[PDB]
Amino acid sequence: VNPTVFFDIAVDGEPLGRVSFELFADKVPKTAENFRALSTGEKGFGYKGSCFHRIIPGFMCQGGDFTRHNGTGGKSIYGEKFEDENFILKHTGPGILSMANAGPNTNGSQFFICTAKTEWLDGKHVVFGKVKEGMNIVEAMERFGSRNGKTSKKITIADCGQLE
Image (tube, rainbow, N blue to C red; front, top):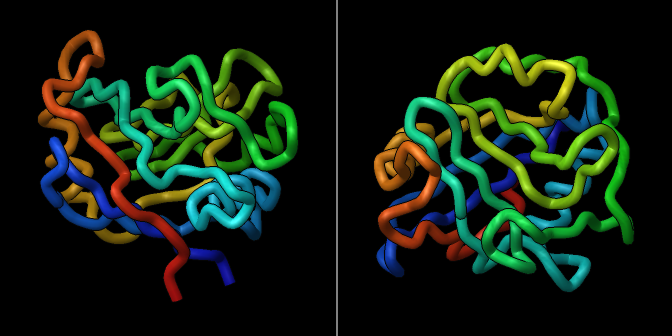
């Protein structure tokens, strides 16, 4: 019953591969529904064509700023930033999908994919999904990052949507 969404990733316009996610709507429905909707585009805006603007190897890949493309923008489907739903799910290793924010109760559209266990984020960022297929594609993306997060090639979500 948990929805599945996919990203088709490109690297300087050239296809790289597909990552798919399981969204934990059974445990974090508001947060899962935000990410699901932005991925399908059904509200008229969303992740299609946006980039992963901050990638730090061994740590995480951050994306979802579809309005300013640099970490300063993005917006939720709710017309304002929304609350931390809960912290039931923990940051337990690679593939964890978690919300970026600017402090408590400031969730918008930016998210990250962990590429290593990030225990110190528990209780600060809402975990709401996990990579299901294509972790190898996230690992390929990771190699285009750097110590300060700048990417050496443009990493884009060329297409996205809901599976099954």
